[PDB]
Amino acid sequence: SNAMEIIFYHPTFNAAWWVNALEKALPHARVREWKVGDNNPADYALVWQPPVEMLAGRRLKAVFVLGAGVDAILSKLNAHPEMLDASIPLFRLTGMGLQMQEYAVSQVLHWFRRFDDYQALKNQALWKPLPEYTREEFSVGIMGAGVLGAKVAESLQAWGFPLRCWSRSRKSWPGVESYVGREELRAFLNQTRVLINLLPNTAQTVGIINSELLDQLPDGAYVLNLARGVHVQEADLLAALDSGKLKGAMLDVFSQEPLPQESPLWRHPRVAMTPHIAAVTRPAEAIDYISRTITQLEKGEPVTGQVDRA
Amino acid sequence: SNAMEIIFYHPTFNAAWWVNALEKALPHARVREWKVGDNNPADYALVWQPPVEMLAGRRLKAVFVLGAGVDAILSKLNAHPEMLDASIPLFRLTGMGLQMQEYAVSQVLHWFRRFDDYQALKNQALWKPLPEYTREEFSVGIMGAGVLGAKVAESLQAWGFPLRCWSRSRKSWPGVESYVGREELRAFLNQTRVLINLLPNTAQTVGIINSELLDQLPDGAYVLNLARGVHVQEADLLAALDSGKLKGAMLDVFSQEPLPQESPLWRHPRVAMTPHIAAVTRPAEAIDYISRTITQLEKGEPVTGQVDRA
């Protein structure tokens, strides 16, 4: 023919910027942003929250999901077996431990040094040095196995906080007490001052952070949600913040995103919020991965990052 | 006689708690909180902002200043040569690098990840992922030589920020570009996104952070003041925050402390404030130092932490 055709679709990224970087990364490719009504052939598709008509009936060499988190797309494909011929390989971008570390280390220290309290004191123009928290009473509990959790634990134990992790599978991270299964969840929660959620999702963790879990945390605890919005029952979180069970929370993810303006979370004085930016893959990195993987496919070499479509 | 008499005075600490810990640390000592009119002998005096009548005419084996920062007391003694017989040794408690590190690392990351911006966006109930800052453009500049500055630099370069330091004396900290003298101050400021002040004081640094210095920082910079209040010209800081020269500031120290409620700093939305708590010596540590040093003096052994009364 024989030009390589690539199509690109993202709900909120700058298509122009991505099309460009892609053109320079794969100079021998024709890249174009996909728009409704575009049924001209393509060899590779780069997508996030793609509509059905973009991929339905397409013959493609591969689809690249623009982000980690294949749960959303897999369910659209599984609820629409007709959206992507099941023989087409699907890929995902996780090398973002650093980003998580930055976020968690900043906030855990922020809370440890009572900057949240000091900000409230500032807003009342009240000079009041507060009692200091001991490292011993400031235990960190990470929920979730996987590199992100492992990286976050590593970076926090370096500051001397007691660390514990909880997962369904038994684990052995250096300098961390490992708790396993719903059987050991209470023991884990009882001893955790700062609860950090880094669970990849599961049917078995939906709404896991609800009142039944919050009740086992010691009073004056904190919740840092870096995993999935559906892991937190928002009404229960707010109730725990209002009763004093929780001193504070920081949430990067929400049950519904963008979080509707109507949500009271926006309004709570002891909730901090970030619009799902804890760890985004740098486009340069994303582009390097995608171009590298396309090259391996064109040459029949081994690839990495393929998502099994169980 | 022969009981060892110790007297204690602090303007805001819990005298009872300190007297107690002291009694247990030196069981063989009689410790008492000093109150106006108490002219009964003592062997050692533990003080912070002592009034003249507490130390005038006293024969003492040593005075212990309850904190690092001997500038305040030395000037009261030097302006009142009659407050402490000049033959009496004076001691000070610096092993607080960790505390500074916690503070600086938390805040520099806080700013780097735009949590300040995200908080403002939260307060407007506006979901808006913001552009990310590169590490390259997020250079840290530490003013001041000495361990605290060295510790803070060490902990920040570990996160991959470009680091520079400025002092009057030439220095060589690993992984840090060293700038020396007022001659190289502009070059240093021009390249510094986050200015961290850790200068021990000098006549030559009073009001150093004024408009002439702020003007050399790149727009969108930040100031973190962890050293002395008199180092910052508060009116100029506020002006720099209002013009956009400075995106934000965090201050742990102020020209006058407690900062009068009248000060506009309390009121600025892009100033964060803490009541001089960046690095306080743990009382347990303070007590261990003082008891250890008293024991060395009683036994004629070498001591450490003595302040020359030049």
Image: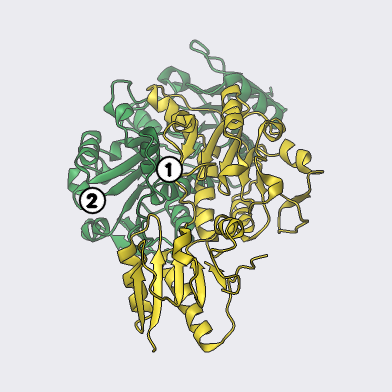
Chain colours: A yellow, B green
The one of A20 and B107 positioned closer to us in this rendering: A20
Q: Position of residue A71 (x, y in %)?
A: 59, 56
Q: Nearer the viewer, mark 1 or mark 2?
A: 2
> Between disc 1 and disc 2, whose residue precedes?
2
Give the residue displayed 55% in from the left and 60% down from the top. A97
State the quadrant of the N terminus of chain B: top right
Image side of residue A126 versus residue A215, left or right: left
Disc count in the image? 2
Q: CA distance from mark 1 to mark 2?
A: 42 Å
Q: Does residue B173 sit above or below B306 in this rendering?
A: below
Dot 2 amino acid type: Asp
Instruction: Give the secondary structure at mark 2.
Output: loop
Q: Badge 1 is on which residue?
A: B308
Q: Badge 2 is on which residue?
A: B219
Q: Does residue A184 sit above or below A116 in this rendering?
A: below
Q: Chain of mark 1?
A: B
Image side of residue A214 versus residue B304, left or right: right
Q: Does residue B41 sit above or below B231 in this rendering?
A: above
Q: Quadrant of residue A125?
A: top left
The one of B147 and A264 positioned closer to us in this rendering: A264
Decide if residue B88 is in sight here: no
Q: Position of residue A77 (x, y in %)?
A: 57, 60
